Image: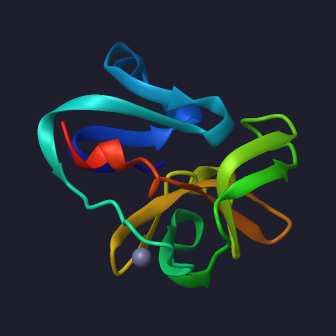
Amino acid sequence: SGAIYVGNYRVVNRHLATHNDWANLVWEDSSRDLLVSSTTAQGCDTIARCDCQTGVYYCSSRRKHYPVSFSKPSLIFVEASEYYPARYQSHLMLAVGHSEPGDCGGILRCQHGVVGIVSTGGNGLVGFADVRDLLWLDEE
Ligand SMILES: [Zn+2]
């Protein structure tokens, strides 16, 4: 589980979104496994605005923050998980690392802020849904 709280936005994995999230929907994209909802309270998270490919992500299944190198956001085939069929996912970044389904929503950060959230796993890779292109999270 996990979310990004930037301004009056909450960013979650679309597959983990709640009824409240859907009742307060701003934007969602199945192909990216992202959903953004509106919040009453101001969040304090900063979204990274950069092309960094090194960062640190939180892995709940190991209670560990792992430094990782990660790929550029791309359209990648993802094998079946417990929450999606085998399919293409867009704006996805891969690293070598541990990811179980319960690790979805772990934050990946660099010196510039939040890069993305864990969205995929298996075959010894961890996949992160990028958020750095969503410049509208910074305003309004
Ligand atoms: Zn960065």
- Nearer the observer, 54 or 136: 136
Question: Please, which residue is most extreme toward the top here?
Answer: 23
Image point 47% across, 53% down: which residue? 133
Q: Position of residue 70 (x, y in %)?
A: 64, 75
- Nearer the observer, 55 or 57: 55
Q: Where is residue 122 in the image (x, y as percent from the top left)?
A: 80, 61
Image point 57% across, 79% down: which residue? 53
Question: Please, which residue is most extreme toward the left here?
Answer: 41
Q: Quarter for ligand 1?
A: bottom left
Image point 69% across, 71% down: which residue? 98
Snapshot quadrant of residue 84: top right
As displayed, is residue 105 above or below residue 49? above
Snapshot quadrant of residue 82: top right
Rendered image coloring scheme: rainbow
Image point 37% across, 21% down: which residue? 25
Q: Can residue 116 be seen in this view?
A: yes
Q: Can residue 64 be seen in this view?
A: no
**For residue 128, side relative to residue 48 (left or right):** right
Quadrant housing the C terminus: top left
